[PDB]
Length: 192
Ligand SMILES: CCNC(=O)Nc1nc(CO)c(-c2ccc[nH]2)s1
Image (cartoon, rainbow, N blue to C red; front, side, top):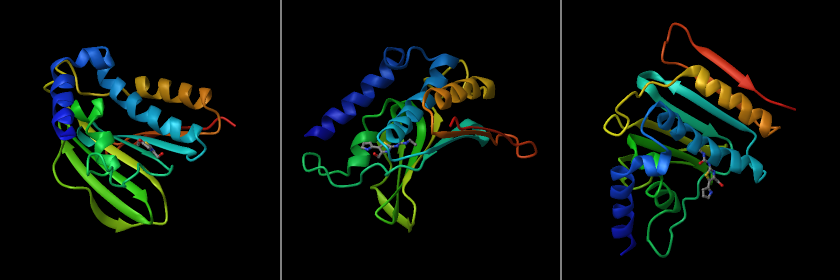
């Protein structure tokens, strides 16, 4: 019933992307990071996280990690599906990513799910145990949407990360570039 409406939401994001993210240029590419990063910042603001890490990985994957409570995994009654799937199958980032995955550390458990263009590739799966909580999202921007470039700009990321850390004092926000294995760069910001 409500799975029909999830599907149509994805078709709608993918047909008119600029209506959701501003554009499909370099600016909109970087806007995907901001959308993920802002959820981590809200978690810190609610009192539950103090560390966010943004990694530019090989092939221009992005990984965003925080140490908050973990996206919830409980079964929504009205979908029959785990909360984390419901939130992610209505995410613009996910819809505009050729691939994306999520790891959630919560309830001493590591849960995992993957998607392509917003569509789950399998049911949320328990994959491990943990004594931490938090959320990891890694995603690969869709080249079919972002036709100008899918290459991130370290200084573009760094300037905005430094400004977010300055504006949201008490959060440690760390940027790392790992695209070049032989020269890894990292800048780490933590005001008060
Ligand atoms: C890597 C990006 N991080 C991230 O999304 N963190 C988040 N944590 C929580 C736990 O409250 C989130 C939440 C979504 C709906 C309810 N809770 S969303």
